[PDB]
Length: 85
Length: 226
Image (cartoon, rainbow over all chains, first blue to last red; front, side):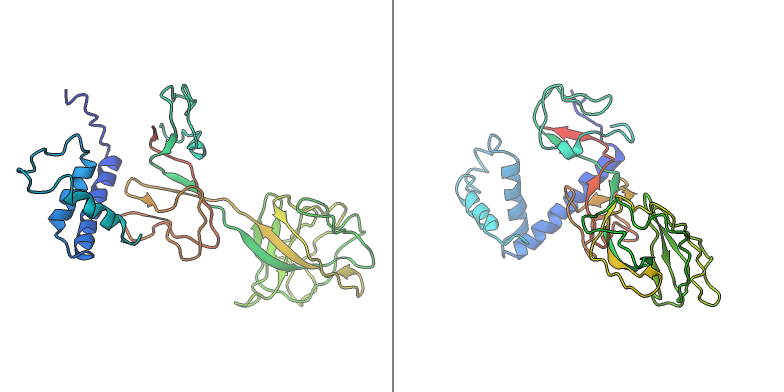
């Protein structure tokens, strides 16, 4: 049903999206650094939230990441960071 | 949106069922208009300055209760006088104007404007500084309605009152946004001398702000409603 998919990725669109990703990572880098926290860690976070909660692995490898607790902790932190950051 | 098609981006304020979008674009699916992919964007740059003139001397021919879009001098047989400071003629444009720049040398040597009524002979006006520009002040010499004005400085000594006042006007413009470009600026946001507006891959020749610029976007690739 990948036809229900909108492969309407005109060049202009593909493009746009592209940069929007790199930048996204570059950011993560700043972050981790501007935080002393692991980058992978970060994006891992970034995901869950964007990946919605109806999708959170009920078993993050069985408690690996405290999907419901250690998570927000980070959020309010980042959120509690200056605009620039 | 086809190319050049666009109607309600400055109305991304709201959207309704069957909301009219583009000649051939509809919107039953309610919500709010959203900007998507620009291509064309106007840029008005406010332009202010000062000028020195020569009008009806020993007579009142202008009242303060006047603004942008009225008369100046009127039916004086015949205004054709001798000025005495030339340069490099350069006539500017208006919806009703031809202003003269006098680049004698590199410096701003002289400033002269001619509202509807005064005929600006281009390069004619420079040999032995005789007010050679034989402009003809006759009748209703009105002013373009596009630029406000005030603070007149009339000086009585002979035939024509040398005036000086405030010249405030805006001036629309436009530029294309290619697929790789990106507006940094939002909804008609203000712009300054050194404030980069839009960019793209080529650091070379990308949207560079200037003297008081304002935002207006006109050519999207699409629109979102939600």
